[PDB]
Length: 393
Ligand code: HEM
Ligand SMILES: Fc1ccc(-c2nn(-c3ccccc3)cc2Cn2ccnc2)cc1
Image (cartoon, rainbow, N blue to C red):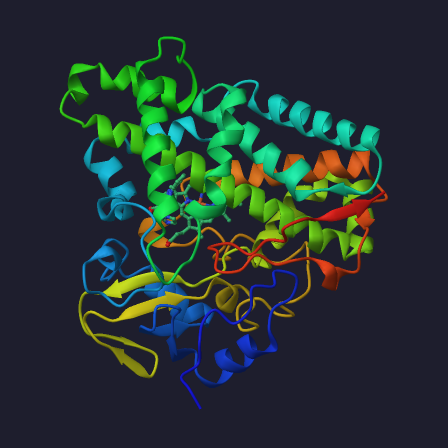
């Protein structure tokens, strides 16, 4: 037989039995990626945390020419170090302030947007597609608001994403076409005097402030493209798969409908059990480092399997169960850990909380309109998502 291939399954509605078998028998295991490279797949909570908390397992070095690769780059190689570049430019605090859910009126905007989307689905009549006509447009609208860019520019930026977040063995020509176009758009935004709010309004001011005169225009535009894309793909995909998990648990759906104060705890468990990330998080070793029974060598690729950690019964007893009273509820790895912990975590939580609260109020009888096996799972992509999510209510 051949070396075990990753990823195991593109389905986001169930974890393969194989994950628990691997975690028990070989929590760091050699695998082959879609490029043909070998990698170490890490699947226990303890070892996933170790890798994420040791910067000698480097994100930036995954972009090096000649490295073993999980998948092809979809951005210029310097952009792999995007957060590091933002920090080196003195922009980290400002970027992170702009993308919290705390700006006045933001939560109300999200509730209003969710309720409008849902009212339109009710008017049109069942079946409704909760991914294309709810979760993704909600994500897109939220990120236009957060960035300060016109709502009407959202759809075109959004349509880059089905290519931009591919997990491909080979370079993708369309990813460069869309990247270059979206960078030109964000560069125009920075020159547009009407853009005075959100992340892009703040970057536009900092760009003209003397304390940032040597930061490149390229970096300013890149922040807009990267934060829009990462935020929209992550929140739309997470909310979509969380809605499936909720729909397939009518008792929990009814509990959260009846006691919406429990929605934050419910969303935190839906984060823990989420299968949205299609691949392990990649890192390149910059030293020889012992990880469990394996001495990982300098230059080797390590893949941190989030569902490995998050379904580890040694950390989360009865891991497949949504339990709203766990003693360690935010200790999951859904947002990563360590140097590269997601800067959008609070915004992603709020997007999903508000989306679920609105859906349960408007569509308390929401259910799948097709058998669950009829959902079409996107392949060779950095997220697991169903192409359509047909529901009735
Ligand atoms: C529920 C929604 C979200 C989830 C589950 C999620 C998850 C993650 C995870 C697991 C990582 C770690 C990557 C790694 O270590 O290799 C990450 C990184 C990142 N996320 Fe999120 N994310 C979400 C929403 C957002 C939003 C809304 C934004 C921006 C508006 C965002 C921006 C980023 C960025 C920029 C990084 C890279 C940070 C770095 O390299 O230090 N994320 N995210
Ligand atoms: F810190 C970040 C660094 C890079 C990106 C990124 N953005 N885009 C993109 C966003 C919109 C349209 C086109 C492309 C592609 C990537 C590459 N990527 C994917 C997962 N990790 C890195 C986002 C955050």
